[PDB]
Amino acid sequence: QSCVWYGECGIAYGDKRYNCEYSGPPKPLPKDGYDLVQELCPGFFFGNVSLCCDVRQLQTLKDNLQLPLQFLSRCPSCFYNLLNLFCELTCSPRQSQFLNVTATEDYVDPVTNQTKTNVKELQYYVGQSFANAMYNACRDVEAPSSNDKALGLLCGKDADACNATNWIEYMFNKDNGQAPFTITPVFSDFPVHGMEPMNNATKGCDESVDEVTAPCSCQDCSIVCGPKPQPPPPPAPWTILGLDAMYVIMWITYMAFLLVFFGAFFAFEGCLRRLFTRWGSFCVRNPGCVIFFSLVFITACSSGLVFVRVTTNPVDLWSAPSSQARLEKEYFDQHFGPFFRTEQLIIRAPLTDKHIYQPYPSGADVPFGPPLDIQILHQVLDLQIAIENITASYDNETVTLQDICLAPLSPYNTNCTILSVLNYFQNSHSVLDHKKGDDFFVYADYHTHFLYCVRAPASLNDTSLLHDPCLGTFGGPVFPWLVLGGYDDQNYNNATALVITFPVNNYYNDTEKLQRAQAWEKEFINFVKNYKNPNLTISFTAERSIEDELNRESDSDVFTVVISYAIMFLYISLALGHMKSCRRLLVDSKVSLGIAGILIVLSSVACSLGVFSYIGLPLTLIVIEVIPFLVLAVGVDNIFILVQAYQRDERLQGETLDQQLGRVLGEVAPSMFLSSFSETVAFFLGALSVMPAVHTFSLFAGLAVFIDFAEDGTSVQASESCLFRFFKNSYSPLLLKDWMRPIVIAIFVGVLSFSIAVLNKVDIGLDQSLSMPDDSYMVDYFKSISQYLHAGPPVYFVLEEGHDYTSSKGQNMVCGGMGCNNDSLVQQIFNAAQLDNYTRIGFAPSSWIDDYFDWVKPQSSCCRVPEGKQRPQGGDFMRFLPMFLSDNPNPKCGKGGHAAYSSAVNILLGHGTRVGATYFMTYHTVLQTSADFIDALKKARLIASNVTETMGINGSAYRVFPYSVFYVFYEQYLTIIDDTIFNLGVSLGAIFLVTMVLLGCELWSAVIMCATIAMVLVNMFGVMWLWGISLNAVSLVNLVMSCGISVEFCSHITRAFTVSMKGSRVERAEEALAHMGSSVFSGITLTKFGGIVVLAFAKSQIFQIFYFRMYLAMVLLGATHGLIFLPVLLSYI
Ligand SMILES: *[C@@H]1O[C@H](CO)[C@@H](O[C@@H]2O[C@H](CO)[C@@H](O)[C@H](O)[C@H]2NC(C)=O)[C@H](O)[C@H]1NC(C)=O
Ligand SMILES: CC(C)CCC[C@@H](C)[C@H]1CC[C@H]2[C@@H]3CC=C4C[C@@H](O)CC[C@]4(C)[C@H]3CC[C@]12C
Ligand SMILES: *[C@@H]1O[C@H](CO)[C@@H](O)[C@H](O)[C@H]1NC(C)=O
Ligand SMILES: *[C@@H]1O[C@H](CO)[C@@H](O)[C@H](O)[C@H]1NC(C)=O
């Protein structure tokens, strides 16, 4: 083994040295060079480390690595072979085999005058295969942020002219101003005149350099690339449903035809109860006090229980508690509580054009969208600074953004967190205004930094001539997707919108601090609303917009329903007693039910919004049945009055009917104890139902009687009219309603198929105020970013190997997410992840850093490591040490010094084994619809299952958690399918069982009433999934009420028809329905007559425009079916 040089001699040019000629054997490297050799040329680091280089040469090699690193650092395999080319030249103990000195000159030591010899030039015999592999591993590497190949910057020519041998030739030519002296390469896989070319093994860009150094990426490599995604599923059925409906229709038609052809070819208990009731009445018919006294008692119980009208309604608790939805939210809290909320603005520049700007030294045309005009950025910065300076007052105190913001690096840094493109310029007008240029070029400006910072937002030093940091003033990177909108692919320069985001404390556990934050928010909303700049359109996130709009909009419409309620109760008042006899009752009846309900609920605590539309419209049941019992008696007139004339007309039609009506109602509201977020309003009303029932018992009858004994004339006429109507109805049924009845069946059939073959969750569409609209419009337009978090809490974490396995799970999750997409982009996640396992690794790779104590004090630097061999081991496993260091950070360590810390961990003392709870979050955009977010949530749950299902263990111990400002809120829209089927199902049983608690005709009554259950439902669904309909936490309650009123109708028509004393074919039926038809047109008609004022009327928002919309449609359909349904059933019988 022999050298050609050893050590450094004279200056060549600049700061550059020739090496000293030396032709002896290699020399063991001093221990003081072991770090350098381990770092640069670890292949030589064994035995006596006998090399043809000294420590000075290795230091010089390290110092010269800056420019290759500048362009190749991202692809370690590419850089590795290059380093080996230089290591072999500099240090190989067999230099003489592949190097031949070709020029020299004297070196004279200035002090001793001893002569040595500069190696001025030499020839280097490089393997052909080595050179080609070195080029091959680097040829796809892309410059840090640039569609140009890194080799175009290291080859003295463009990448399309760069080849393996001319690249090496260029690097080795002193003319390049970097190489200290020229090395002339000769490329051969064969010996050349006894020289044995350097042909060291090489690594491709698809290979790992070592155990702690991964292969190169796709973006910077070719070998390790592909394949894209191919898991797209395409479903689409439905026609089947249509065919079935059609088939059914055909069958029906056939049946009808057949029928036509044929015609051409040819109880005790109940009674007893009634009797008892009558007896009671007769007794009661001997005193008014008792009754009223009872009403008075109810006046108290109702009002009494209403003590402390604390009937809350806020804030966002309707998904109900318990289960996973709530339990999951609570869990994430104990670990961190409320991650926090964001006030967010989207900003566009409608009066500004795009523009071009060549960035040195490429000079390629890069277009920049309207909002990235330099002047609009200055204007957006002024907006931003003004927002930071907003103050609100609460009590006598002042509230700033600095009091409520996420300031991640407090106290050492109170700097608030503002996600904005202006934070790439540290929110500084001057810094952004800067621009290093001369008479010839602009070398660096607000463009270069931008194009660099979108690729390296954590950088504390632009690689351009500006040398400005990218890191935001809050101490963390601002990711480009989260601050720009309306750009294509990752061409952030083409953005048509800026997004500005301020995280502020939600203060879920602190009431006094939350109120202060909400005071600030109100000022923020005001500031934005009144901000004047023709150059910018600014639009909303906040908090009140969604909470203030609902409480600010939902009011005017009140006057609508209110009015309608009055005009309706007026008619129902005129109807029967007309005068001041019936009015009193009702007013008391409606009050009793409403008052009683509030009292029944006060004994358990509860409250709600829709709980009002139900309470009011629900009261109808009490009025309807109550409005027909009195009317029927009015139509009475025999040998008796008051005495038996009241018990024979009351305990005869009111006993059974009412008795059955009250039950069918209590069964729908009573059994409302189910599982969901509506049982409260439900039960409360159902309870108010028996109450309202027992009320109108002796109260209405007695009162109506006690007092019942121009106005008279009017009553008679109405009665007469009713009678006439009944007669007409009878006549109609007499003819033949078989054809139309079949047609009706068709309508129901078509409805079931059209209603069962549509569906939907529920979106958010509030009135057109302003704020809310802005946020809704901005969201629709924007895209790519704006977020929620998927999040896991994990336990244990102590077995180096289980951490490696958990990291593989984590990396795999990042992949699927960055893949799963839809239409023209991903849907699932976003997405990507920054747990921490990578931070530790980074630390291991590198080194220390300075911490500067606040306000003053000497600098503190402290740390260490642990390479080379150990380095790989340390990073591989163990974790207490790393963990306790990694949690305490706030100043990088290398070429700069910034902040790169976080949170989520919280062990005790130095028990690193007890660490919790690491949390990884990938924010994904959506804002599509109630069904869109629900679909994404559905995917995330399966993602959580897949990760937890992959590698589990013992029983239970934490799992996946998808907490996104949309869950708990949409969590309900999840089990909506089971709810509807379960909710209605529970009523179908309570109704079929109740209607039998005083009958049990097997198929007679059972089917009669049972048919009404599916009869009306198909209508409600049709209108909902058919025309102007909807569905949600309310619609579900809507369907419930529908089945309720429906039961009411049927109940009366049927309890008196089924029996039928003097029985017949279809004659007795027409007789019963007659006395029941008059009431069907009274309450029903009126009720509709009221909705119209509510439905046919107007409003200032679609909100109720639907709620009270279907009501009238669904309520109307049910009423119509009442008469038809009964008639059809009778005929069938
Ligand atoms: C160039 O290749 C040679 C031959 O593989 C490397 O020398 C070997 O290095 C390993 C790793 O330390 C030792 O185990 C062998 O004993 C060495 N063999 C010989 C013949 O010396 C050398 O490390 C490579 N050069 C560089 C810079 O990595
Ligand atoms: C202009 C760009 C492409 C140059 C990129 C390659 C540079 C970094 C290369 C070209 C020639 C190389 C030098 C070749 C010879 C020596 C002598 C050695 O005893 C110390 C290292 C040193 C000084 C090398 C450092 C790296 C070097 C300067
Ligand atoms: C080195 O190669 C050159 C030709 O390039 C030759 O003239 C010289 O004699 C050789 N010296 C040695 C030691 O091989
Ligand atoms: C879940 O992972 C399993 C393998 O464990 C895989 O077969 C399936 O395609 C994955 N599904 C989703 C939705 O990620």
Image (spheres, rainbow, N blue to C red):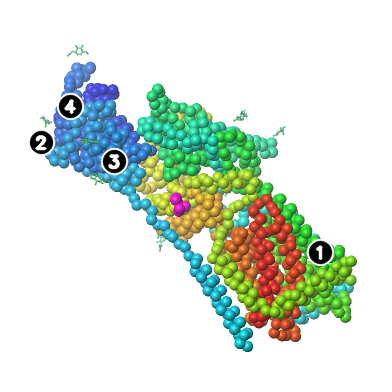
Residue mark closest to the camera, 3 vs 2: 3
User: Vertically, is 1056 above or below 326?
Assistant: below
Residue 618 shown left or right of residue 443 in the figure: right
**Rendered residue at 64%/41% (across/down):** 522
Depth order, front residue of 96/353: 353
Q: Is residue 202 visible?
A: yes
Q: Dot 3: within a 10 Å radius of its alpha carbon, few (fewer than 14), some, or many (20 or more) residues?
A: many
- The residue to which callout 3 is attached is 139
Q: Which residues are magenta?
A: 822-827
Give the alpha-carbon distance from disc 4 to disc 2, as whole Å.
22 Å
- The residue to which callout 4 is attached is 21
User: Residue 1007's spot in the image, x, y percent?
Assistant: 64, 77
- The residue to which callout 2 is attached is 193
Amino acid type of the residue that numbered disc 2 sits on in the rendered structure: His
Q: Residue furthest front?
A: 264
Q: Quadrant of residue 85?
A: top left
Residue mark closest to the camera, 4 vs 1: 1
Give the alpha-carbon distance from disc 4 to disc 3, as whole Å.
35 Å
